[PDB]
Image (cartoon, rainbow, N blue to C red; front, side, top):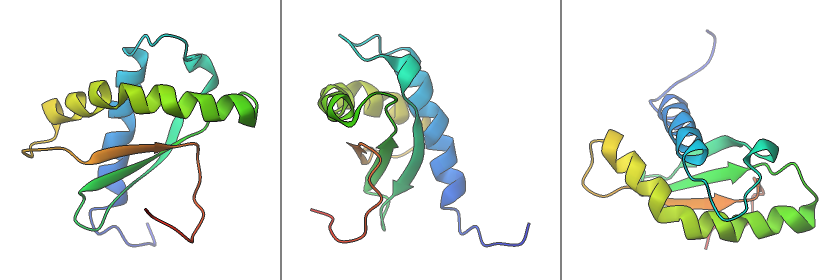
Length: 106
């Protein structure tokens, strides 16, 4: 096309589908998967962290609840990526309720 690549967004798009297949196989206590997606994914400088933007299709009050269910499910997600991604350990999959907002990291 007309724009840069740098092996960033392509890799994040590879991780994007992985997390969705994992979600379809998560089963969960009560996550209405029909009312969510994982759209934006952005990995860190040294790819040691992986920021996953979760867009719930409920109210914002409900949307918050889903993030703790996701953060419980972290190990199930991250182990699946360690099947596919040839590296020793995998990034910290930090789930967020779709918050691209420049100020913080923590």
